[PDB]
Length: 131
Length: 134
Image 1 (tube, one colour):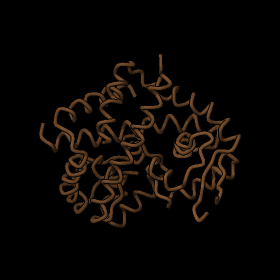
Image 2 (image 1 turned 135 degrees about the vertical axis):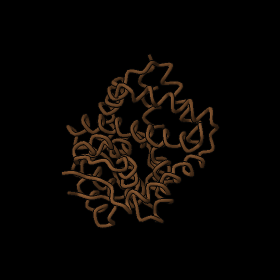
Image 3 (image 1 turned 90 degrees about the horizontal axis):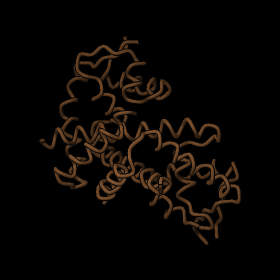
Image 4 (image 1 turned 90 degrees about the vertical axis):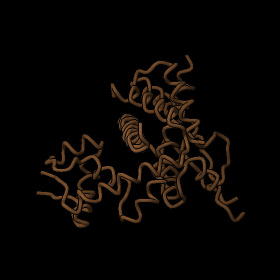
């Protein structure tokens, strides 16, 4: 058994891990005037993809309540185009390259080896697989 | 695996893992009018522990900017008590805060059982995450 104990540890560690990751991203994203979730949205929208807000909200796990305002924000900064069909603008498709360099930096700060990273990846792929 | 590819997979998998976990917690926490972060604070505060608000911010990785407004809400529901024992702000669980933590703990078990990973896989994840958080 001990599911109570394992559960508590998973609870804690997933919570702490996301907080530490997010915090480090916030630092790098400030220079682009973007939040963690806005960054996630921009990377989750493949270049030249015409998605409807509902489908986007399913991919990035965001309810319309937070998504709608987020899209408005990315609307003015002019990174996405709300015609509801959503897509990346030209300057929007642009930043996806330098933003793509930021995750490498954030995850290096945790200073884990390539093997450890690969093991974590394999564990999470399994944990999430069946949702 | 280049660091770019690995970082990308970590980015995605941590984001999704976290989101799938929150979702489930939110669904079961609604009937208590508690948010996932509210639940985290409640569980972070030990019963009979008159904790300093900043010591709390450290273990819960929240800044007082967001920690303060939340403590106020939990205080309204009579689960927590803010006492100025004497220039600092102390935080403690009420009798009701202690009681509710019983059913709240069962939720965390329901949440994770739903992912259906084995005890061994769970230990692997914990071990890998302990190291990651170092």
